[PDB]
Image 1 (cartoon, rainbow, N blue to C red):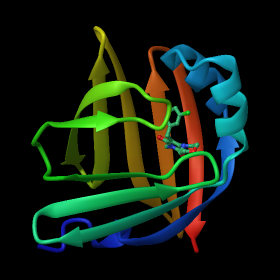
Image 2: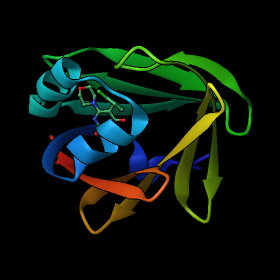
Image 3: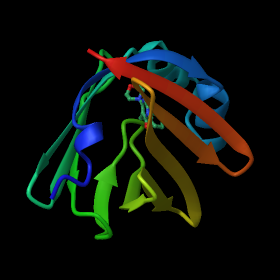
Image 4: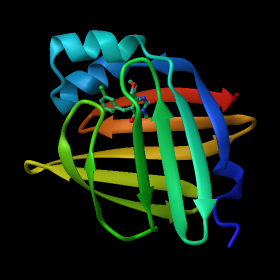
Length: 134
Ligand SMILES: Cn1c(O)c(Cc2cccc(Cl)c2)c(N2CCOCC2)nc1=O
């Protein structure tokens, strides 16, 4: 109860850094990188009991995940990877690990001032995606 309150809401992308390089490291192909890199998603986060839902809506792709913290689930990512994901809360940060084909990437979401800051890491490459309230 009240675990993720400060995440709940409707958020819009305001800045991005190094996302194309992150996508390259993940294995995303040229055309998907270009179209996906243009997107300005909204991220809609809600909680109902133990179930957290994160929706992403953009002109590129609309996706939605629902999950319970610590409980693995199957996810098809916007770039069409079929991954096994687990999301946990670590010191106030939502930590989302995706595993596929012997690879792994981690997406961290944290509240910083009035922003929701998303850090995506694949090996040595980090992208930072900043969202603000819609
Ligand atoms: C944190 N984050 C994110 O995880 C994705 C999904 C994603 C991950 C890896 C490769 C790709 Cl192509 C897309 C994202 N996209 C949502 C769909 O429209 C394009 C932007 N924006 C983000 O801020």
